[PDB]
Image (cartoon, helix red, strand yellow):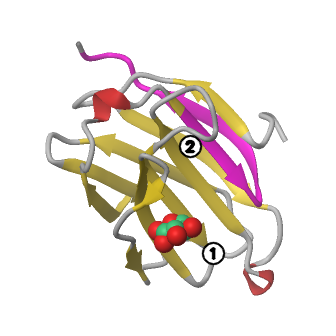
């Protein structure tokens, strides 16, 4: 809807930064829609990924990083706070030791930094969703 998907935005992250994403799945969970959020080191899609967050609605969540063109140790979670056919609010906060992911205001996943957050230069949100809001908090030094 509001914003185009794939959605790409140049960004700068550091401790205290928050990325808020608002959207909804394009189809019911039965058809297994996906949602993917990648924090890139460069403005290009082929660049490395500091934090890869992929949701298979109703199934699982996978997190990883792509370093020097290679995927690393994948982390899998079965925690599924997302609701079928519902708008969701996803917020990713940058803590000193890791990323904390909140879904609709509830802590749901964390991922220890593998690469310093300062290496991020772009964020891309894509797959099967309509995007209504994308915001990066630049209120701290
Ligand atoms: O999430 C999908 C993507 O990240 C995983 O963590 C890795 O195993 C990659 O091989 C895979 O292509």
Q: Residue furthest left?
A: 97
Left-right relation of 89 to 30: left
Image quadrant occupied by the N terminus: top right
Check if residue 127 falls in the magenta segment: yes
Question: What label does residue 44 carry, if any?
Answer: none
Residue at the image position 39 percent from the left and 46 percent from the top: 92
For residue 4, above or below residue 49 = above
Q: Marks 1 and 2, how far apart in space? A: 16 Å
Image quadrant occupied by the C terminus: top left
Q: Residues within 10 Å of mark 2 (few under 14, many from 20)?
A: many
Left-right relation of 63 to 14: right
Q: Main secondary structure of the magenta part?
A: strand
Q: Is residue 31 visible?
A: yes
For residue 46, above or below residue 24 = above
Residues rendered magenta in the picture: 123-140
Left-right relation of 132 to 40: right
Q: Residues within 10 Å of mark 1 (few under 14, many from 20)?
A: many
The residue wearing badge 2 is 21
Residue at the image position 77 percent from the left and 60 percent from the top: 128
Residue at the image position 29 percent from the left and 58 percent from the top: 111
Q: Depth check: 20 or 122 in front?
A: 122
Q: Residue 139's image quarter?
A: top left
The residue wearing badge 1 is 57
């Amino acid at each position: 809807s509001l914003l185009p998907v794939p959605y790409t935005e140049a960004a700068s992250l550091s401790t205290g930064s928050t990325v808020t994403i608002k959207g909804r799945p394009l189809v019911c969970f039965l058809n297994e829609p996906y949602l993917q959020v990648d924090f890139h080191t460069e403005m290009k899609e082929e660049s490395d990924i500091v934090f890869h967050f992929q949701v298979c609605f109703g199934r699982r969540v996978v997190m990883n990083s792509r370093e020097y063109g290679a995927w690393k140790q994948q982390v899998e979670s079965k925690n599924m706070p997302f609701q079928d056919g519902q708008e969701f609010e996803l917020s990713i906060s940058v803590l000193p030791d890791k990323y904390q992911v909140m879904v609709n205001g509830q802590s749901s996943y964390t991922f220890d930094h593998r690469i310093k957050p300062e290496a991020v230069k772009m964020v891309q949100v894509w797959r099967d969703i309509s995007l209504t809001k994308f915001n990066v908090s630049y209120l701290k030094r």
